[PDB]
Amino acid sequence: ERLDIFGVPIDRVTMIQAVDILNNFLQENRLHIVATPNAEIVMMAQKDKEYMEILNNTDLNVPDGSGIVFASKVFKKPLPERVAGFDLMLEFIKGISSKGVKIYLLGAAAQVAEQARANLEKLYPGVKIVGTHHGYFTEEEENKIIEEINNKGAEVLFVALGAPKQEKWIYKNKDKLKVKIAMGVGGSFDVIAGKV
Ligand SMILES: CC(=O)N[C@@H]1[C@@H](OP(=O)(O)OP(=O)(O)OC[C@H]2O[C@@H](n3ccc(=O)[nH]c3=O)[C@H](O)[C@@H]2O)O[C@H](CO)[C@@H](O)[C@@H]1O
């Protein structure tokens, strides 16, 4: 089902299979960790002993970018299509925004996460974004944020802290968090807020 690229499992999925897998994940009552690796993450994975351990315990590693698909041309069944990890995030919010699935946005510089919430509520109307918080907090604050994420009954956590911080922060709190999908989506808040 998956492809071993220099230690990093990449699931052989299309945009639509990846959106379908993620929809079935919301139906299973456990934390799923989704990551979107590109060639640059796989190179990071070689120097970072811990990051590699993490990329092998995620529930879904979705191939981000055209470069990593190119590398797959060495394998027997190469990766089927160009998936952009940002497109995956947006096509995903399109589908759940009618069904009222609660989304929390943790990350980005001060007031950036709040602006991305606004533009999403327009593009995908009726989307339930239950909370946000900037990506610069303390160990004291972390407990407060996680408490909010859990108590507001968020099913989807979009962590925008960049690689590999986002994938590492999720894995540490993989037992504290009570959401169904926690997906590192680094820097896509900056894009949606129009800052970048
Ligand atoms: C799609 C994806 O996985 N992209 C990654 C990329 O993301 P990026 O383009 O955003 O690059 P950064 O320079 O790391 O950006 C930092 C972002 O995280 C926020 N942040 C950071 C630190 C913090 O303590 N709190 C925060 O909130 C900040 O506001 C901003 O949104 O980074 C890697 C290296 O470049 C890439 O290899 C990798 O593909």
Image: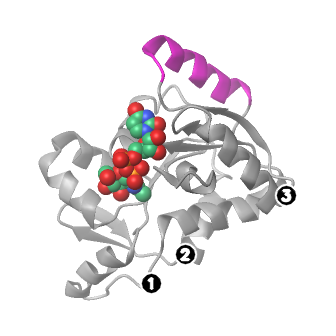
Q: Label 1 amino acid?
A: Glu
The number of discs equals 3
Instruction: Relative to 39, say whether 66 is above or below.
Output: below
Residue at 36%, 81% in the rendered image: 79
Residue 170 visible? The answer is no
Mark earlier in primary sequence (3, 2):
2
Q: Is residue 134 left or right of residue 58?
A: right
Residue 184: horizontal and vertical position, in percent? 47, 48
The rendered magenta stretch, by its main secondary structure, is classed as helix
Residue 125, label in figure: 3
User: Quick check: marks 2 and 1 in contact, CB under 8 Å?
Assistant: yes
Residue 149: horizontal and vertical position, in percent? 64, 29
Residue at 84%, 59% in the rendered image: 98
Residue 15: horizontal and vertical position, in percent? 55, 75
**Is 133 in front, or is 20?**
133
Q: Label 2 amino acid?
A: Met
Instruction: Report the magenta residues as a range.
Output: 137-152
Residue linked to disc 2: 15
Image quadrant containing the N terminus: bottom left
Neighbour tally class for label 2: few under 14, some 14-19, many 20 plus, Cα within 10 Å: many
Residue 161, label in figure: none
